[PDB]
Image (cartoon, rainbow, N blue to C red):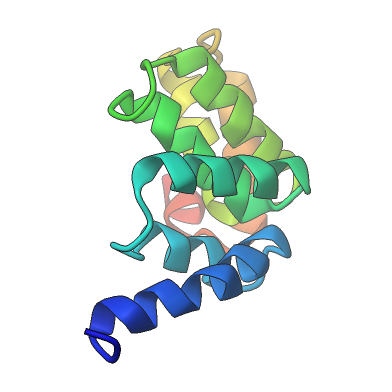
Length: 133
C-alpha cells in the first residue's frame, strides 16, 4: 500500500498545485487528471491558482461552473473565469470565450466581439480559432 500508483499520485499533489499556481505548462491539467484529488480540493486549488492570476487555473475553474456537477451551474460565472483566463493570455480561455460570445451562453450574444476574441485566441496559437476565422 505504500508504493502503489495512488501513493505516488498523492505525492505529486503539492507539486502540481505549485505548477498550476505558476501557470507552468500542463500544471493545472495534471491536477485535473490526478484521481487522488477529490473535486472539492480541486475547486479549492484552481480557485487559489486563478486568484494568483494563473491563466490555466481560471480556465479550468471556469469548467466547474459551466458544467454544474460539483457546484451549481452558473454560465455567467463560468464566462467570467474564461474571460479572466483569456485576459491572462490563456489560449483555451479565449477560444472557449469566443464560442460563448457567439452563442450568448452565460454572456450577451455578440458575434462581433466573438470574432475579436477568436482573433486573439488564434494569435495565442489556437489553430481551431484560426480556422474558424
